[PDB]
Image (cartoon, grey):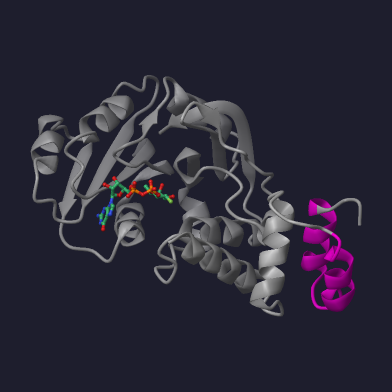
Amino acid sequence: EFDITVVIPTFKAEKTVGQCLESVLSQQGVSTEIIVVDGGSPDATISIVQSFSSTNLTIISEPDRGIYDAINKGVSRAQGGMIGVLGADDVYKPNVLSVVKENASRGVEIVAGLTLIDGQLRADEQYRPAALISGIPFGHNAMFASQEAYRKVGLYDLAYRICADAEWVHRAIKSDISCRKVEQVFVEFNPEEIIAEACSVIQRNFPFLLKEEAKYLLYGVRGWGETSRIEQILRKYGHESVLFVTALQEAFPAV
Ligand SMILES: C[C@@H]1O[C@H](OP(=O)(O)OP(=O)(O)OC[C@H]2O[C@@H](n3cnc4c(=O)[nH]c(N)nc43)[C@H](O)[C@@H]2O)[C@@H](F)[C@H](O)[C@@H]1O
């Protein structure tokens, strides 16, 4: 019934959620549905959201098991063709939703754009098998996925409390979900555990890898590490998966 659905997970977001809603409602050229999924905010968050009361806004307010649990609740209730996810501290740039609708009007299931973090562009990678040995290739809040994309790929894995977004995009890549990357800015806004989750996601792609080998690949793709052992890993596991070989050949063409 809508062109776009925007899911906004919130908890104690009274300080910015108004700006976020303002950045969405001022988008021209599209019919939009907004689903706010609140984890039971004790502050004014709900009172600010109701100030934007409209027929195309839905408020859920109940306890949940985290950001991706609230995201799953909102995606499940989405009624628009393309679904995006926006945090209360983020904002969409002008005309971004019309761009999404036009690019998706060709049947592409994912439309992703650039992300502005502290006045710098996110160091994006390509949406391709080479990302399966890295992280999420583009900002998650800059991504719009169709109803079909979610229906085929599924919901976010709550086992990953940090990198559930990267894991979902990696499942979309593996499912051959079509993706179009627009070179325009769409959104502006325990590290060892981040590394552990990233390596576990990579292992879910290639279950034959040890954790240290996945970490080596990750750092190699992200320019954080060395690449002298890549040929050793390829010869060792190349027989296991053609997709593993393709990911290594795209990431390290010198090999
Ligand atoms: C939006 C996400 O953000 C992630 O990283 P990020 O660093 O931005 O986390 P952040 O906490 O700053 O924002 C989280 C947003 O959900 C709200 N929030 C926080 N905790 C809870 C909770 O328990 N329950 C419910 N219902 N909402 C909660 C918070 O108010 C804010 O609106 C990205 F990795 C990810 O791809 C995604 O884009």
Boundaries of the magenta span: 228-251
* Residue 209 left/right relative to 59: right
Q: Can you give x and y, in whole percent of width and height, for residue 203 in the image?
A: 63, 73
Question: Which quarter of the rendering shows the C terminus?
Answer: bottom right
Q: Quadrant of residue 238?
A: bottom right
Residue at 91% in and 51% down: 254
In the rendered image, residue 78 lying in the magenta stretch gets the answer no
The vertical placement of 38 against 167, above or below, is: above
Residue 102 visible from this viewpoint: no
Residue at 83% in and 71% down: 233
Residue at 31% in and 37% down: 89
In the rendered image, residue 247 lying in the magenta stretch gets the answer yes
* Along the viewing direction, whichever of 3 and 242 lies nearer the viewer: 242
The vertical placement of 34 against 245, above or below, is: above
* Residue 192 left/right relative to 208: left
Residue 172 visible from this viewpoint: yes
The vertical placement of 198 against 3, above or below, is: below
Q: Can you give x and y, in whole percent of width and height, for residue 201 in the image?
A: 57, 67
Q: Can you give x and y, in whole percent of width and height, for residue 239 in the image?
A: 86, 77
Number of numbered labels in the structure image: 0
* Residue 116 left/right relative to 204: left
